[PDB]
Length: 188
Ligand SMILES: [Li+]
Image 1 (cartoon, rainbow, N blue to C red):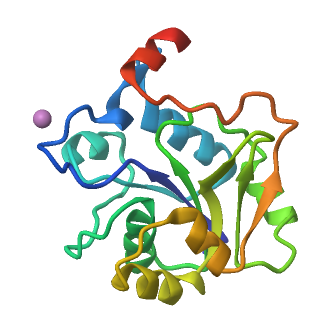
Image 2: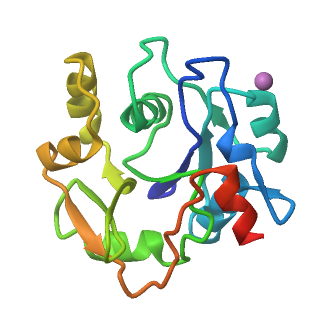
């Protein structure tokens, strides 16, 4: 009953009993993934989170937590597909859990600039962010086919799907990401 579902991508795997759970690192007292979720909720009514570890902790703020399928596909596309398989509705705006400053016109600008493409993603003037992406339902079968073929590459898929980058170079620093605890410490 809303047009785009927001999705925080809080990682998959735990390919050695985890290591740092990046989405749960706290920035000014608030988990990174919750900064992203709050920024999506500014612009969208329905927001969910894809998380595969510490699910009870992710569930604490009252959002639906979606876990990856048993297929255990590699990389960020696996979480995208698991979310499309477990949520109805025609459009999704994905964003990783480590980019806490995403802007309140993310959804609106990606939608304005979609120009008939089934997928668009953010370019920040320096680099593509192909996991910050507005994706139509139609992508679901293509994603399933690509991951079943054993592929993982995100940009390659976005290209195969007929997507394009949307220019957010004027949004100074809204797309900085926290790569490590070492980096997080600097933004406090
Ligand atoms: Li642990």
